[PDB]
Image (cartoon, rainbow, N blue to C red):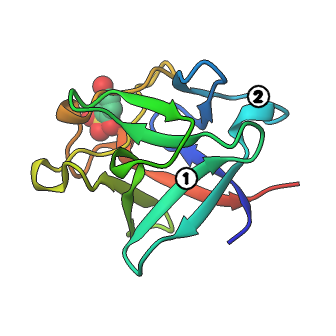
C-alpha cells in the first residue's frame, strides 16, 4: 500500500477524483486530487481512494467513473499487472463486460463500454508519490 499517482499512458494524465465526484486526469503533478491509496480487499481486487477527500473511485451502470463517498460494490476493481509495469483496472460489478477504468487523450474519462484490451486509455502506471 501507499499514496500512489496512477499515470494514464493515453494522454499522459494522472487519474484525478475531483471533490464533486467527477473523475478525469490532469498533467499537473501538484494537484491535490491525484493522490490515491490502493487497498487490497482480496487478492485480485483493489479499492482506489483519494487521500485528499477519502472518496473511492467507482464505475456506475453506464460505465461512467465517479467518486463515491462510501465504498459500495461499484468501487471494487481487479488490478492486473501488465506488459510494461502498467496496470489495468476492471470494474467488478461489470467484469463480464470488460469495463476498464480509462481516460481519453484529452484527459476526459472514457466510459467503460468504449474501452478494450490493448488501448492506451486503460493502462495506468502506479507511481509512489512525494
Ligand atoms: O489505444 S488507442 O490509442 O487506440 C486509444 C484511442 C483513443 O481514442 C482513446 C484511448 C486509446 O487507448
Q: Residue at x 55, y 24 (%)?
A: 21
Q: Residue at x 60, y 62 (%)?
A: 38
Please say if 37 is above or below 75.
below
State the image coordinates of residue 129 (x, y, percent, origin top left): 80, 56
Task: Identify the secondary structure beneath mark 2.
Answer: loop
Would you call the spot at circle 2 few (<14 residues within 10 Å), some (14-19), or many (20 or more)? Answer: few
Q: Residue at point 36% right, 75% down?
A: 44
Residue 81 shows in the view: no
Q: Quadrant of residue 53?
A: top right
Real-space Cα distance between discs 2 and 1?
Answer: 19 Å
Residue 29: give x, y in percent of width and height: 79, 36
Tell me the tag on residue 48: 1
- Relative to 106, is 112 above or below? below
Q: Which residue is mark 2?
A: 28
Q: Can you give x and y, in whole percent of width and height, for residue 77 in the image?
A: 37, 57
Q: Vertical placement of 31 versus 129: above or below?
A: above
Q: Which quarter is ligand 1 in?
A: top left
Q: Is residue 104 visible?
A: yes
Q: Is mark 1 within 8 Å of ligand 1?
A: no
In the picture, measured across the screen, residue 5 lies left or right of residue 24, that is right
In this view, the residue in front, 58 or 117, is 58
Amino acid at each position: 500500500k501507499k499514496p500512489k499517482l496512477l499515470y494514464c499512458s493515453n494522454g499522459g494524465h494522472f487519474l484525478r477524483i475531483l471533490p464533486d465526484g467527477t473523475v478525469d486526469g490532469t498533467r499537473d503533478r501538484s494537484d491535490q486530487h491525484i493522490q490515491l491509496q490502493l487497498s487490497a480487499e482480496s487478492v485480485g481486487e483493489v479499492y482506489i481512494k483519494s487521500t485528499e477527500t477519502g472518496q473511492y473511485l467507482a464505475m456506475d451502470t453506464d460505465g461512467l467513473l465517479y467518486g463515491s463517498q462510501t465504498p459500495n460494490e461499484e468501487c471494487l476493481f481487479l488490478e492486473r499487472l501488465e506488459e510494461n509495469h502498467y496496470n489495468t483496472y476492471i470494474s467488478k460489478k461489470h467484469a463480464e463486460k470488460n469495463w476498464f477504468v480509462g481516460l481519453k487523450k484529452n484527459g476526459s474519462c472514457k466510459r467503460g463500454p468504449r474501452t478494450h484490451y490493448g488501448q492506451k486509455a486503460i493502462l495506468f502506471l502506479p507511481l509512489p508519490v512525494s
